[PDB]
Image (cartoon, rainbow, N blue to C red; front, side, top):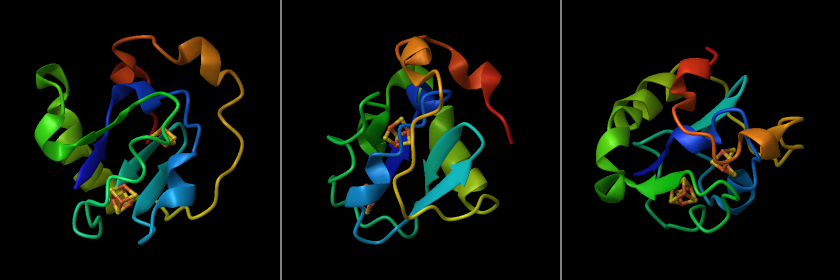
Length: 106
Ligand code: SF4
Ligand code: F3S
């Protein structure tokens, strides 16, 4: 599975969903997650993310390991998103800011 990590929080560009063949992205107020059992590891989404927040599971940075299980848990409770929508209104201000997990909304 591929995993969405910190820098998606408060950006949520949603470019990643247009390339996913199996539609395994789930939507939260201000972040997206990949459902691990549905992802077929095609790697097509990782180049699409403007925030470069998507990583192959095996390449998730050492200080971002919690996102692995967080993607799994939140994918069981958030709704499925299959279409690109507009970025969060001030996505570019937050793109690049570190430690955004403290701002995650359920
Ligand atoms: S690797 Fe492919 S299947 Fe997995 S989320 Fe990305 S685009 Fe979808
Ligand atoms: S910001 Fe998040 S919504 Fe997709 S395009 Fe990047 S993982």
